[PDB]
Amino acid sequence: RVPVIDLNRVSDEEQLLPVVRAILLQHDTFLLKNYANKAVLDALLAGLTTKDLPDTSQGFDANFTGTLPLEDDVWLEQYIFDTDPQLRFDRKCRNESLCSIYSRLFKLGLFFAQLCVKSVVSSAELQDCISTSHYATKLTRYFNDNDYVTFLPTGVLTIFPCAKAIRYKPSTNSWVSIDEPDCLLFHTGTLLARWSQGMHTTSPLQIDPRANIVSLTIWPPLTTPISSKGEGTIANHLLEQQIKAFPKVAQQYYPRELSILRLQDAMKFVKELFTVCETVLSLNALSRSTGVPPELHVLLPQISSMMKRKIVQDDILKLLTIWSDAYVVELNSRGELTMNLPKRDNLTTLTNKSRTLAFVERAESWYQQVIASKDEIMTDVPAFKI
Image (cartoon, rainbow, N blue to C red; front, top):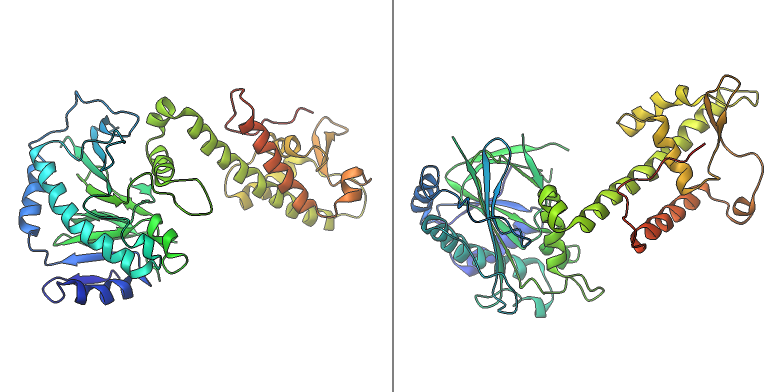
């Protein structure tokens, strides 16, 4: 199940470090038991159910900060803060109740974040990336006016004051719900896994947005480079995560970034489709003896089954857009589309043996041409006209 740290048994840094480290080497999620202010914390959360309502006049900006109306009378209240005065992230939280929860979750979360880094991060220069003077936080509150959201946190760790209405993936596929109301829940983010350089891995979580969930995620300063081998920062990963969580907000504030992420899903789609089509066509060719190409409608159900989704004739035509010489697709005797492997060689097949690598290489090429051009980039691969 879930690793549990009892604070009445282990309370100081000397005791907690080997415990935290042993956990982090095999887990990304753990419970905090007997926290000295669990009662006060639970009282504050209870207060949020009837008072200190979300500021509906606040708006929701490009920093993914403010108040956002969701469906089913659910309200999101979120604040992203950074210690850097050069950054316009000045608000940690708003109302007295949320501020009290923040102060308790931060002091606790900052302590354990440093333990997490000390545990699985070898770089001495990264041992002090997070301090009381250098950090960034995201305080998230869901409010319900009387399904699960899947996300992958990107901080060092995310804390939940109550281990309730949250699902996770055991390290032993399938979601399992966590129901330990007397404990806080800790989950590590991708930054810790990344900086561990293989020592630690994390996993996505699931929450019920109608269960008044509160969470605090903690980072080093947002301007911190992810790695020496790149220019991407924590800000880039935070943005991508927030875009995936709130795509409609993204469509307004970050339309290009959204359309790229959507196009990448289309890329992933067409690559698997090609591999599936290769298998299906190869198998069908075995149940033949004469050079009569199969009608496309015959192949679709098998292709759809392997793709685990409905695949239409239009989808297969996307493959030709990426590589027109991939297949020979034409109308038959009775006006139905047929599909078969090419018989004759061209300059491509005379110089490249692998059909597998050929499609992948031309998929990325097509992908770059779209995102390098300044014309309105598409979110999908256009169907090749016959």
